[PDB]
Amino acid sequence: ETMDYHALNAMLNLYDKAGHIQFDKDQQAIDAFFATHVRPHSVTFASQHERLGTLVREGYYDDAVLARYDRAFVLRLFEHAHASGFRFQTFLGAWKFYTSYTLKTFDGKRYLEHFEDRVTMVALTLAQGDETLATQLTDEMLSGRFQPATPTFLNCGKQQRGELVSCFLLRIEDNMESIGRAVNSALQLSKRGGGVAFLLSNLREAGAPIKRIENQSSGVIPVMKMLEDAFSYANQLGARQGAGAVYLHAHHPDILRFLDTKRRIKTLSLGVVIPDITFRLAKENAQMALFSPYDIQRRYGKPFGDIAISERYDELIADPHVRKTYINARDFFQTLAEIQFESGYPYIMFEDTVNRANPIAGRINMSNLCSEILQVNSASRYDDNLDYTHIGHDISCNLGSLNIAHVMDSPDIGRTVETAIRGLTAVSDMSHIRSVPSIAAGNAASHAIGLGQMNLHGYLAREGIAYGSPEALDFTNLYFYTITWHAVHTSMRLARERGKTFAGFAQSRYASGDYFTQYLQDDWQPKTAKVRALFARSGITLPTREMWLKLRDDVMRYGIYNQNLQAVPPTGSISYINHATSSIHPIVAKIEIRKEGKTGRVYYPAPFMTNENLDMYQDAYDIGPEKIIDTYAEATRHVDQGLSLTLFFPDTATTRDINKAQIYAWRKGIKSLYYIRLRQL
Amino acid sequence: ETMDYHALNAMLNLYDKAGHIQFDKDQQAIDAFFATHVRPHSVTFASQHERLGTLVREGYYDDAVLARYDRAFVLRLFEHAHASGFRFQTFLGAWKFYTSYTLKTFDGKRYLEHFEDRVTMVALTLAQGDETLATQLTDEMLSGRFQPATPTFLNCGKQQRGELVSCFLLRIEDNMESIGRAVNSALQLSKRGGGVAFLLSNLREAGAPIKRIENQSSGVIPVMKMLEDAFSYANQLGARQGAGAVYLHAHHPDILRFLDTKRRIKTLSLGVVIPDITFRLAKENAQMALFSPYDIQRRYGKPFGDIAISERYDELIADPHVRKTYINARDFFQTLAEIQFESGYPYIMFEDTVNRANPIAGRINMSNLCSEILQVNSASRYDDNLDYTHIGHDISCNLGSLNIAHVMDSPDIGRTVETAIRGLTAVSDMSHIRSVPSIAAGNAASHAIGLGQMNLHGYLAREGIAYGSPEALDFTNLYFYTITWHAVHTSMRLARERGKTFAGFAQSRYASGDYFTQYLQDDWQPKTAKVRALFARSGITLPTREMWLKLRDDVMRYGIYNQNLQAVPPTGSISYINHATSSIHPIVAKIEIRKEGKTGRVYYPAPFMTNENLDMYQDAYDIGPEKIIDTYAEATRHVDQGLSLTLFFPDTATTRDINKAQIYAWRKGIKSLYYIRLRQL
Ligand SMILES: Nc1ccn([C@H]2C[C@H](O)[C@@H](COP(=O)(O)OP(=O)(O)OP(=O)(O)O)O2)c(=O)n1
Ligand SMILES: Nc1ccn([C@H]2C[C@H](O)[C@@H](COP(=O)(O)OP(=O)(O)OP(=O)(O)O)O2)c(=O)n1
Ligand SMILES: [Mg+2]
Ligand SMILES: [Mg+2]
């Protein structure tokens, strides 16, 4: 007799005379949802075998995927799938999946998939015919241990579908050709829903020459302006703005005009690269010198974006063949925070930290639209007709995440990590982005992937450890320690199985073993009793020196398949499906509210949370930056790419506050910073 | 003792108690210019031979051009050149050429060319080694009979230089690829100073689908928006806006949003194609039906831009598989004039008149930034990586003009026309625009050129005939009649010499002779005594039936080299150098004032004009549209492409006035209309 699941949902938004919540009311919502809406609008077939048939016949499922398997095997899988006992844990989780993920009939009126169907098809797709693999992926996803990126989760198997990968990073070179190409990539990538970031640092600055006639270039903005229109023009079906980003080196002469667009470029996001010296200068209240990329090129034969500024600052200041401009470092960071304060951006990439941690030959000069990807890239050369004469290497992202709790809840952690790695790797292998050759090239050369984490705050709460605490820090350090061991063990394996390794391996730190010197010392003993306890209870072995030493041999000898393994992005709405917390930070709220749906909003309580443990769920605001920054650093120690890191502040905070945080971060090893969020309603 | 040439110039701007002008004062200005400024800042070498040497050595002249000739021959030419007796006729003519055309040293401080040097190098360049040709071109240019387009005049021979051609017309196709390419062409062409127009009619309209999901396309504007930024970004060295245009069919569903950008797109110009039916509808106060290009394609397998609307209006109205929208034709033309009134644009291309007059297989769906070029074009197909899989045919302009007076002043009119044609043809042969394959293709396939006219009003005045008059109309009809005969005789010749013809010739009207039926009847007798007189006095024979009949045989048998011959654009500042009137219309003023120079302005009196014949120089305003429109029609009868036609109106004029004029034009055969100019200060 009460079947308004929204109402029921709404009830999570109520507190009783004792500041407690009717969590059950949310479970009632799930129940009414399935009963009043799903079950009734979901299609039931007489058998799976006819269902496939129909789905392929009418144009929904891609038969090419089913065809890599003996159909019996298929059926066996759907059955297992549906036999696993999967339930959604929350009304939003369900509602999200059916309103935006599950496959519907072409007219919208009926559902054709349920969570496990989708799971299955994903498993089938990535396993490319490998049945045991297919089974495992199925298992990993149904257990909650693994959660592929949205773009994969959503399209695998579908006949009419998106691409499986969808954030991309591109260079631009200081000539029109590159520029033209960039704008064209923007168009092609964004029409298909991709997020794309562009490096701008190589471009000659405002005022520089063209064809040896002085004061003629107009710098980056008018280029920013084009990319902007592109993204705005080429939305994705069912969207109005597209998403772009541009990164620019802080020491680039146009830095301030650049920052200035946000005090005008309304939809691209900005990101700024900052080397260590900049910090040095502002400390010692000094002047910042900006070098011309025009000159830099002619005198060094390389582009601004490819030299090491910190390492050649003085040199450069002294080379009179390099024009210099000066602004006040302290004011810089001031402008930086003022903007950040007004609008979240810009992101920040600690260039020196990054390159110093980079195990891969080359430098890293830019990042993605979520500031988590960090990888080398390389120039492309064109022909006057735009035809590539030299196809360089650009970057694209293959993502998925583990839900730490569920991982810890299963002793075979090595299987668990191997699978995800196997799956993301598949995503990479199946990927062939034709519209932008340099992307295709890159993928193909590197098989880079980015395995990421989520639900930390979820986990720690459940185990009664407070976010931020030494218990917490200790755990996050070792968890990531152990995840790294298995992932590289896995990539090593793959190289063996496939008998090849990523391009450049040889020049890498993996090749020489220097990549391990870190692990052959000691941290690795649980700084803490509780943490020691958790791993033990979980039946998981923390990798041991003998293990590392052995893996180091196997790597030096056999190599690894993927040039890059981990990356920790924010976990948008999949997190709700997976029932996990945004990534590894804490909980923007206890009962998160989203402005979605026919009622206006929908409410989402955190995992494992009950009236008897609320005190373990203090929100990000409440926890504040230090603790957050501290958690990410423990993680940053191991993750070869980077992690999206937001700082949440009270609306009373000041730019100095912001700046103190960024310094701390910087001082702490943090590779990069994402947006800064001032609390608002 | 008085050497301010500007002052002296200024004096043309003075009237005496009898409304007369000190024309001589302008000659004094020339004299002081050369004496106080040119001579002193121009470089004299001990001999020509060393001069060449130096100019090649230091990087100014291109030796590759000199190398096609025996150096003695060269020298002989410069000498002849300088021996011809050339003088500029006006202070602006000189001042223009030295401030913007002649070659200076790289630091700006000194001149290295004089009019005849430039003439010579042009002659050498186009003649490509042919000495008699080189001589003739020299002669034709020095006599004033010929005046190549600015881009050629200015760059031929130079080492550091522009392209020789510079207005281009491009299609776009209804898919992203084409769009991307368009924006890239915009960039590449405009960085080098080219004017470029785009067809937009094929693009699916605002609201149409994408990937079979309804209401999803955003039509042309956001595309207009990109092209706009492109042009604005890629100025030409020494310029801030670039120049673009977009054409769109009046019966395209986005027509009104389109017109609406100008009531927001600040720098592209607009142009509208209009078929006859539109006129029919508005007469009979009817509704205009707009057909979807999306549908049109699917149902007819061709793009909006390639079907004949007039011819299939009803059909289309009846095909229910073609979506239709309706707006009121009368209001259309109303909006058209209101905009025109506010801002000059849009240009107008009378599609049916044009295609009906078109001697060439195919249809004509767009025009250039000056509305004078009209030629067929064809789609290009791309690969997902932008690579052309099928290179279509797009259009570019090779222009030059004859100065009617000087032409008439020399009995060998056939030599005179043959040369120009030979020279423009050279421009075409030497042209290889790599950044846009479809342009290169087009040129190569067609060798289209556009020989044009100027100084009509100049001529008629001198011979005491009033602009507009039956004398005038009669002359312009026969002059163009005779120019056509010789140009086609010339192109015919070329095909023979070169032993090939333009692509498609066979499908042309030249091939079947229908191109001549017009000339084999009769008009061609001077309607007038004076006109008969002028040709006679000039020693020029008006082509005779036997002549046409003979040329028709030679053409049917041997073919012609160029697919298109004539085109009559406005003659911007070269006109001042050549000492002629903007094209064939009359004289925006008696003493034209330009806002140029260190004094703020510079004054330019019309050719042959003196206090004893002012009454023959009534300005365009004063003459008004009819007479103008009437002159162009006489011309439109013969010119295979089209002619830029501005109507000048009093600031009291009304949109109805404007609309009456456009109707007259339309009714009169006029192929197209350029901007409408309201008189302002
Ligand atoms: N009309 C132009 C031409 C170039 N640029 C900009 C874009 C590039 O960042 C930079 C270099 O363009 P190119 O390398 O194509 O320029 P060139 O190679 O012709 O000149 P240079 O050799 O001077 O670099 O100048 C511009 O804004 N407007
Ligand atoms: N994200 C997108 C995709 C397309 N278009 C526009 C530009 C083109 O005029 C038209 C056609 O683009 P494509 O042909 O590339 O579209 P498809 O071929 O994928 O779809 P269809 O086959 O539906 O035409 O749609 C757009 O505005 N935004
Ligand atoms: Mg360059
Ligand atoms: Mg299409």
Image (cartoon, coloured by chain):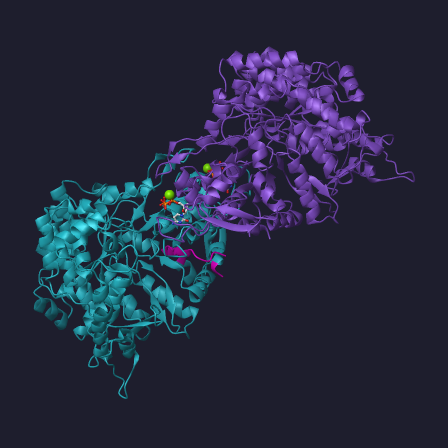
Chain colours: A purple, B cyan
Locate residue A135 relative to residue A601 in the image: left or right: left
Name of the residue lying farthest toward the bottom: B17
Locate residue B195 relative to residue B509 in the image: left or right: right
Is B432 in front, or is B565? B432
Answer above or below: position of B645 versus B423. Answer: below
Answer above or below: position of B262 versus A459. Answer: below
Is B643 in front, or is B91? B91
Is A554 magenta? The answer is: no
What residue span does the magenta drawing correspond to?
A: B262-278
Q: Tell me the residue at 14%/59% (across/down).
A: B140
Is B678 in front, or is A19? A19
Name of the residue lying farthest toward the right: A17
Locate residue B209 relative to residue A121 in the image: left or right: left
Please identify the quadrant where the N terminus of chain B is shown: bottom left
Q: Residue A230: x and y, percent?
A: 50, 44
Q: Is residue A125 visible?
A: no
